[PDB]
Length: 129
Ligand SMILES: CC(=O)N[C@@H]1[C@@H](O)[C@H](O[C@@H]2O[C@H](CO)[C@@H](O[C@@H]3O[C@H](CO)[C@@H](O[C@@H]4O[C@H](CO)[C@@H](O)[C@H](O)[C@H]4NC(C)=O)[C@H](O)[C@H]3NC(C)=O)[C@H](O)[C@H]2NC(C)=O)[C@@H](CO)O[C@H]1O
Image 1: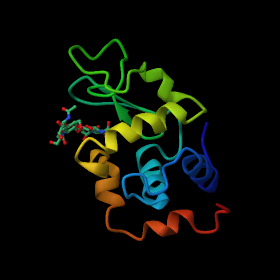
Image 2: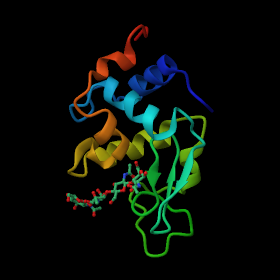
Image 3: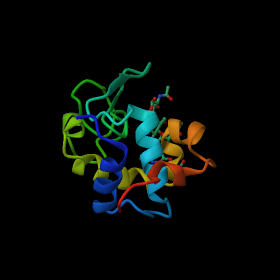
């Protein structure tokens, strides 16, 4: 599913991401925009053989099981395919664990390079929240 900007903001808010760990909703929508362009089915391969899945581009090296990333962890306790769903629940629960891991949103490279320190409020302009 490709989400609309405001559509994703509502689901995210609903799922408790607004100010989760001190990160305003803007931050989360910006991250989704740059990581997958709001596409739940985005997948990308990394050089170490791990894969990034879904809307938040969650990595198999640490967070999910894809049966093909030898000696990686499955910290969110889910098959990576659960992250590709139209329903963002699994992606959001998993995100919550990632962001609390110590590096905050720096875990997301597109956030760090394109969202961090920008006027993230713009991402939710005109949404009915
Ligand atoms: C080429 C490229 O950059 N591709 C992108 C993917 O790499 C990226 O996925 C992210 O991958 C990074 C790389 O390591 C990963 O970051 C690691 O995360 C673990 C888990 O949190 C860290 O280990 C923790 O360290 C903290 C603080 O040091 C400790 O408090 C804690 O004990 C550690 N936890 C565990 C379980 O070990 C690493 O510190 C950290 N490594 C680095 C180098 O920063 C991110 O978690 C991945 N992000 C996500 C969302 O999965 C992918 C996602 O955007 O994007 C590719 O393009």
